[PDB]
Length: 213
Ligand SMILES: [Cl-]
Ligand SMILES: [Zn+2]
Ligand SMILES: [Zn+2]
Ligand SMILES: [Zn+2]
Image (cartoon, rainbow, N blue to C red):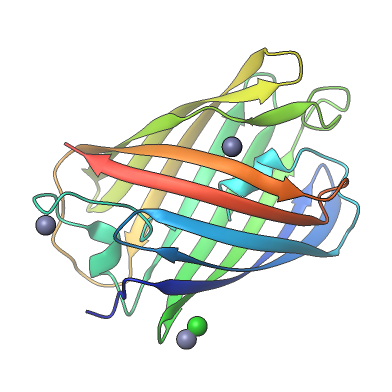
């Protein structure tokens, strides 16, 4: 099909967090049917970033999801035309991130164009003070509403010292053409920063995602 067993990734993110503008470019690759991918990111403008890189990593494509053969795959069916998505991440004490991303295909690769806006983070909280250590593993509930696919996940943003804060994710996924709609299901996530330089100008992200009934 058009979605190959090995797909490359090219992306660019343009964003603003508490008024700090930045641009990040990425390249990577993954195995769409295994639900795995790796992306190598470089800050091109706005370095060094004055906030936690973890608020960006889940914005850096559900085509990289292992799906059982009996659950229609909203994401892979949308190609080559592709899909866009929009997400809000609501943090416990006023921070909010809104993301819009366009996922397209060019031959054996995906291109992402990502716009991200973070606002109202407490200046002395763990996001703006870079006191986070990653995300827990999560489960996203996927369900069709208004003819498009919605996903919600309740996440723990892990903190230095071993605590965490709650972050609620709500995403809307919109195929650019009609596809066969799945029934209610789940996607289990793991995302990790595998390596980074000291101020996260260079970062490698690894993600796994597996759907189940
Ligand atoms: Cl390529
Ligand atoms: Zn099979
Ligand atoms: Zn290629
Ligand atoms: Zn690890």
